[PDB]
Image (tube, rainbow, N blue to C red; front, side, top):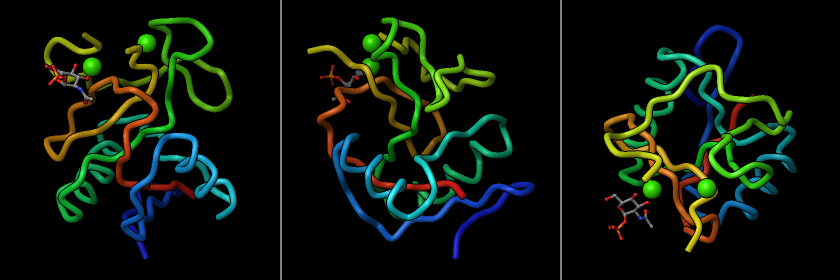
Length: 117
Ligand SMILES: CC(=O)N[C@H]1[C@@H](OP(=O)(O)O)O[C@H](CO)[C@@H](O)[C@@H]1O
Ligand SMILES: [Ca+2]
Ligand SMILES: [Ca+2]
C-alpha cells in the first residue's frame, strides 16, 4: 500500500539507506525515489515521513551542476519546498522533514526510502 496523488503512488517499507542504496532499491522495485512535483505530492510524502518518524530522501540532486537540483531525467525542479536557509563535506542530495520542508544533505546520509510508482 501507500499514499497517492493523481496517478502517482508513494510507498515505503521503512528501509533506511544511503542515497545510492536507496536509488537501487526503488529501481529494482521498478520505481524511482520520491520526486514530489507539487504541493499535493509533497504533502503525501510528508505524511509518510511523519508516520515513520524518519526524514526521507527525495530523488533530486545537484551532482551534475552544483546548486542546480535535477530529477533522474536530468530536468530542473518544477517545485521546491526548501527549509529556511536551504540549500545552506558537500551536500548534493535532498532530505524531506516531517514538516514537509527540504534540506540538502551529504549523499552518504542514511534516510528513509520512499519510492514512487
Ligand atoms: C547532515 C545534515 O543533515 N546536516 C544539516 C544540519 O547541519 P548541522 O551539522 O546541524 O549544522 O543542519 C543544517 C541547517 O542548520 C543543514 O543545512 C545541514 O544539511
Ligand atoms: Ca550541492
Ligand atoms: Ca543543508
